[PDB]
Length: 209
Image 1 (cartoon, one colour):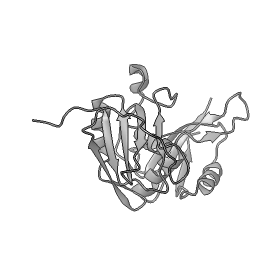
Image 2 (cartoon, rainbow, N blue to C red):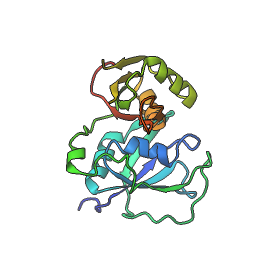
Image 3 (cartoon, rainbow, N blue to C red):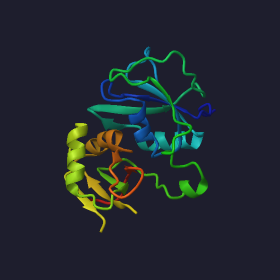
């Protein structure tokens, strides 16, 4: 027999101080639609993540298992529990909600076949591809954001000459993955529009920025 089918992942090795539901979404949304994230008081460093389907679970396991974040190995496994019930929510170490439902997030990337086709699913690398940044974005903007978030500045930034896109490179895969968790969907001032830009990040297969 094979593993019992399930749209729910168990992730172990999350940093108890630094991770929260939104930051988990920030990593896992690269691999499929994220429906729910649940931290459990009884299970330190672990979260259940419900994806849209079993295929998204397969993608997340294939790509994120055995990667490292904040000096810890991430272990991404199929959950024997195939649905998440909220239970009694609590505050995480940062005070944020232990449970979040992302089913209605505008930041899910695989909600339609046309949208899904514009995503490339790749392994974690030391290079992030950014999209939906302001037109006049510079390396300096990224440095300040990283400084303010308390994450490592990228060692190299390329802004490709609506919005800007480009590449952000760190010295290590762990640095980029940590920053992905913090920086994905960061809100940037729009000097010429009604809403700010939601910065969108993906992994790149480009060797360098």
